[PDB]
Amino acid sequence: ATFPSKEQMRFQKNMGYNGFQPNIAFKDDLYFPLDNPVQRQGLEDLINHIKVNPNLAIEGRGLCTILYIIAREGKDEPFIFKELERHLYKFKENLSPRLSFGGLYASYKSNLASPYQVS
Amino acid sequence: TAAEFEQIMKIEGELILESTLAPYGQIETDKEIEKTYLHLLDIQDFSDLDTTRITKEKTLTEEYRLSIDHLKNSIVTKKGDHLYDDINLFIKQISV
Amino acid sequence: GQFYSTLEVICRKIGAYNDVELVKLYQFILAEKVAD
Amino acid sequence: RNRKIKKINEPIDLIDYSKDPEINEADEEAGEEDFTLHQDPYIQEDRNHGYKAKEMRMGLNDDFMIVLLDRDVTTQVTTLNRVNHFRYLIFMGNANGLVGYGKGKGSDFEEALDNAILHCKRNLIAVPLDIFHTVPEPLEGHFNGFQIKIHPSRTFNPWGAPVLASMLLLTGLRHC
Amino acid sequence: ILKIRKYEEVHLKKEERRKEKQSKKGSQALIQHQKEMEDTQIEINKILGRPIDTPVNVPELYKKYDTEDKMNNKYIERYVKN
Amino acid sequence: YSISIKEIKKNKEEFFKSNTNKILLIRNSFKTTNLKLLRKISIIDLILKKYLESELNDKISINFDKYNLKFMRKKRLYVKVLRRKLRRMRKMLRWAKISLRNFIRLTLIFLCTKDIDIFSKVLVKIMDSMHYKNHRRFLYYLKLFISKSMHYYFNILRFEGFFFY
Amino acid sequence: STYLGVNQTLSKEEQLDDWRQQQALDHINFTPETMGKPEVFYPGSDRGPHPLDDPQNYIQWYEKHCPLPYRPLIDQMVQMTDMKITDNNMPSYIKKWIDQIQEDPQEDLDEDLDSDEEADMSEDEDVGLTDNKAQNDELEQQLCSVVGGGQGVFFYRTNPLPRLQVDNTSLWSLDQNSELPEDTSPEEQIINCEGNITFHSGLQDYEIPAFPE
Amino acid sequence: MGLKSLPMLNKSGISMYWHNIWDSIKLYKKYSLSFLFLNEVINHFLNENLYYYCIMKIRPTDNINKIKKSWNMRHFYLGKILFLKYQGWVLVLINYYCSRRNKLYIAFKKIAKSFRQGVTSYVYKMDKYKFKF
Amino acid sequence: KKKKIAKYFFQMFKKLKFKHKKYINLINLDFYFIRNKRFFRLHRLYDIRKKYIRYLNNNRNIYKFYKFRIKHNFKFIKRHIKSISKLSIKDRVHFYELSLRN
């Protein structure tokens, strides 16, 4: 008989210990586990980091990802989107599909985005 | 020890010169005396510096805004006007 | 550092060659605005 | 106050009070220089530096060769183990009547070397010698089972041990 | 054009003679130059609002920007060398 | 712009005095653009900090710090006194493609910082690149080097003791 | 050029680099399209509107608005301020634009470096106690000392190094994963860049860094 | 051989901080074993460049001997890895020295011609098309 | 001449470079000679009990440079050194130095 057997190998899978999640960061251009309450406080700090900082530099990633999450969690933020739509000229015909999915997905669900943002 | 021994012999070598060398001018003033003890005790006058440095008491962050509002009320503003753009930004650059 | 550099653009087009000259000109206009 | 300016306030060490001798320096330093005369003395500009406790046997001007005679190995027996004390011997002297011998002893051949030289320079002597007609008379020196005999000659006759031909010359005894 | 001239001058004179000097005793440049010239057009495609669809062969356009005579007058050389 | 910088530098050479607060020096931006550096460093948070947080449920701060120690720029006697003694090892040292300058420093970092890990790796890079005939000689040069040359530095650094078996 | 020690003409590739940099300077039309920057005017300063009244503020404003074609010319001008040729004799009309380190008369009668060569690039000059190399030298000579019959000290303790802090604003600078630096690695940047580096999960405005900086 | 009993533990609690300073109750097994998992992850993450590995294979697609030898890290010399706990904050101190550090922050006559007439007199092309009789 | 001025006859002409000098050291002044620097060199080996075969063959094959005879045997060196081994050192110089050859 073989060792390990297949019925055994599922035990380690069902519990979930076969994965190594930092590899996901290289697969997905957006990656925010939020597996802990401390990690969630790391999200609210960003939201206050923006409200306090009127002068701000970005890339195409960090913009789109925050919108994906705020949409996923459903938080209301009428101030965030107008602050971030200014930079969208910077990344026209450049963004990844996974990121282009995010800000699209958030612009709909937010009920707060502009008709320029969706465009 | 050795280092303790240099400290002995070297004082003797230097004081002998004063025995042969003429007497020299000497200090009199009380303030001038106290600087010596500070020079000996490794203390330094630190208090004089904080007098200069700023505090949140003396700032003017609100008194700017009171004056700018007097301009907007007094002066006409339009998109063509060069002041309209900078002032509406200036208002955000305080309240934000 | 946020609202400083714009005053240099504003105060010059006003008579105030510097930031503080605004205060020097608007002393009494501003003093009436305060009540303590 | 004046002390704390001099850093004499607390104890201090500026002098080198060492007696570590000088041994085999300048292994490669620009080769040689042109030969000049000894006319520029030293000045005691510093009450800290000084040339006290500097031996003459190291302070001697002229330069020597060193001569090998033997290396051997010994044994000391103990309860647990045997130990080897490596040995070395050496000879050295100018053509002008300076000469010496040492006995090296250590845990390596290369160390008994470095020790033996230390003994020789301290074991130096000066021989009576006139450059003109070095050897007036014959001589005899007998150690156990051994004896050297010199007779004067107007020329030099090195026929024998090539060692002693050098040793006799590295004293200055050219007429022998 | 700065990439073409490196290609035409450097990468050919090397790859030609390297292959020649090696073929007596016994591909990236053709492709990587195409990896790069295909990038120069993309920005030019963005300027006109005309996507990658258009071919953006460079020398067709450069001819308008330089009307300079490609050589000098011979009389001046005689006139000055004199 | 060019005429500016000369009058800047000539002021710098004369006007500088002893700094009052050294802690202000922390803000000093690097030669690299502090933003450009920050672009080429942001990757680690999602990899390491955001993961090490997962395995601990707790806040993190990581500090890739350096030593406060630095070395002179000018060769002097007190470097040359060491180079003359450490010559026979140079042959053994070239096998490892290790420099001479660096070997002297790490020992003084070691005698000061007292980190067993540093001076150990220096040996292992030597003792491996060599052949198994020659280990015996390398130590006899290392025994003299520590016992004679560097035995003097001990009392200065409040350092006392060495042993290697 | 030869008195200074200027080199000959560079390779074709670096001559082609000299080509377009002339073209940039040659294809001007005084527009932001030809520049790469909009148009501005000097900030009239306190000491005076002329820039040399405060050469510092000129440098700040000039860098922020330097057009693309004029950047390489500047980098060559920076060299002139640094090239310090030495001679006891040099013309005066040249002396305006370069330095003369006066050799001592009566002088003919009376630095640490690597040993490897496989490295691609040469070293950083680490942060000193002060910016002036000469004033650094005067200070360090007081630190060095003598211990043992032959040895001494040739190394000093430093003022606190510079530092960085990174708490989740990291994200904003972050690039995609489809494009990343394959040549340069962060771990190398941490090492080669001076100072120290700090990540931490974040704080509030009222709060202090956990670790002493 | 004579028995040299445990010196460090005979000395630690009264004269020397352990290699880490933290303490725990009911979780001695995790922290004592988990920091050991992190001592060597960071060592093997730094002493072996893995950012070059995480690019080549972990990432999809759509020098080699130079890395296996870790030539880029030949000057790297780690000293320790340290750990702490307080106030809900885990911490890490990593002191590393390098005996070498590279530079990464990075045709004169052409100036002289265009500035020959003086300081502010630049030669634009629009001037040099001309030729005064 | 830049050397032999600098060593012996330069102090005569030196300028007055003003120098701070501590009064403490100016009392204990004593001018004297210490040591010569041509003789700071190592001491060198001479081993002829064991390695004499090395020296002599190297000494002979040097002596071939003069070519008293093309074919150097141990017969020639015998015959040739008998006669020279008589001669006073004065005579042995003239044979190598003041010959019609030289």
Image (spheres, rainbow, N blue to C red):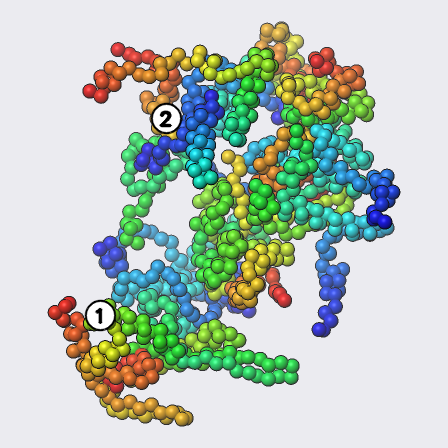
Residue at (45% x, 58% y) in the render: F80
Looking at the rendering, which quadrant does residue F157 occupy?
bottom right
Q: Nearer the viewer, residue F147 or E74?
A: E74
Secondary structure beneath dot 1 equals: loop
Please give the label number shown on residue I70. 1
Residue density around tag 2, few if under 14, some if 14–19, many if 20 or more, within 10 Å: few
Image quarter where the C terminus of chain E lies is top left
Residue at (34% x, 31% y) in the render: G96
Secondary structure beneath dot 2 equals: helix
| Closer to viewer: mark 2 or mark 1 | 1
Q: How far apart, in angstroms, are the residues tagged by discs 2 and 1?
A: 71 Å
Spot occupied by residue D121 in the image (x, y as percentages of width and height): 40, 77
What chain does badge 1 belong to? I
Tell me: residue D117, above or below residue G170: below
Q: Are marks 2 and 1 in contact (CB under 8 Å)?
A: no
Spot occupied by residue H97 in the image (x, y as percentages of width and height): 59, 49
Residue at (41% x, 93% y) in the render: D144
Tell me the kind of residue under disc 1: Ile
Tell me the kind of residue under disc 2: Lys
Please give the label number shown on residue H110. 2
Spot occupied by residue C15 in the image (x, y as percentages of width and height): 54, 14
Tell me: residue F4, above or below residue G103: above
What chain does badge 2 belong to? H
Looking at the rendering, which quadrant does residue B14 occupy?
bottom left
